[PDB]
Image (cartoon, helix red, strand yellow):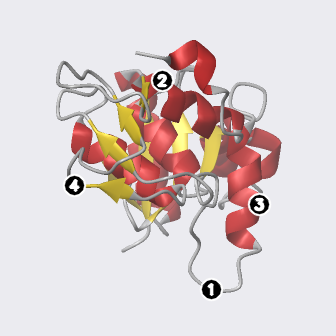
């Protein structure tokens, strides 16, 4: 199947069960990274990986391993919400809900009112991925620092008093709290 499921923070013995269950229940291909076809992200431990972040940005189901075990038991893929990792990632059900209620193609609007952002090439997570996250959550990415109001990540160049210099953590915390964070605590 074209539709993908992504595992994250998943010990290899649980990974083994997932591969077997997917082989038996069908409906998914397992992919290493969250992409346009991913609808379900399965987390083994409650950790904010890049795949969790991308899964949230795309409004995926972010689920516990237990969904796989109960689905095997009951013979088919079952309702996801009882397994959704809402306590660890409050943004997950919010984006997932927005996404399924979306009339057309889903895109988040978290950053829709934010100025364009220049992302440091030295940023962590990697710049291409951090840019993907900004875009998926409704923000605009600038290709150069010139004229950009927000600069994200390590920046040792010339600084302007009318630009905000914010850590990558500002983007990530905004995404996981489903609210744009106050810049104060992310400066430099």
Residue tagged 2: 169
Residue tagged 3: 97
Label 4 Cα crowd, 10 Å radius (few <14 / some 14-19 / many 20+): few
Q: CA distance from mark 4 to mark 2?
A: 20 Å
- Is the N terminus in the top left, top right, bottom left or bottom right quadrant? bottom left
* Mark closer to the observer (4, 2): 4
Label 2 Cα crowd, 10 Å radius (few <14 / some 14-19 / many 20+): some
Q: Are marks 2 and 1 in contact (CB under 8 Å)?
A: no
Residue tagged 4: 143
- Residue at screen point 40% across, 21% down: 11
Q: Which mark is residue 104?
A: 1
* Mark closer to the observer (2, 1): 2
Dot 4 falls on a residue whose secondary structure is loop
Outermost residue toward the bottom?
A: 104
Quarter of the figure with residue 79: bottom right
Q: Position of residue 89 (x, y in %)?
A: 68, 31
- Judge left or right: residue 47 versus residue 50: right
Outermost residue toward the right?
A: 82
The numbered mark, 4 or 1, whose residue comes first in the sequence reads 1
């Amino acid at each position: 199947p074209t539709r993908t499921l992504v595992m994250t923070s998943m010990p290899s013995e649980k990974q083994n069960v997932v591969i077997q269950v997917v082989d038996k229940l069908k409906g998914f291909s397992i992919a290493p990274d969250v992409c346009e076809t991913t609808t379900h992200v399965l987390s083994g431990k409650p950790l904010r990986t890049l795949n969790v972040l991308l899964g949230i940005a795309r409004g995926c189901w972010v689920l516990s391993y237990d969904w796989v075990l109960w689905s095997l038991e009951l013979g088919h893929w079952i309702s996801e919400e009882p397994f959704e990792l809402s306590h660890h990632f409050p943004a997950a059900p919010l984006c997932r809900s927005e996404c399924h209620l979306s009339a057309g193609p889903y895109r988040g609007t978290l950053f829709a009112d934010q100025p364009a952002m220049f992302v440091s090439p030295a940023s962590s997570p990697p710049v291409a991925k951090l840019c993907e996250l900004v875009h998926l959550c409704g923000g605009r990415v600038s290709q150069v620092p010139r004229q950009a109001s927000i600069v994200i990540g390590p920046y040792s160049g010339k600084k302007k008093a009318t630009v905000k210099y914010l850590s990558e953590k500002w983007v990530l915390d905004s995404i996981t709290q489903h609210k744009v964070c106050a810049p104060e605590n992310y400066l430099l």
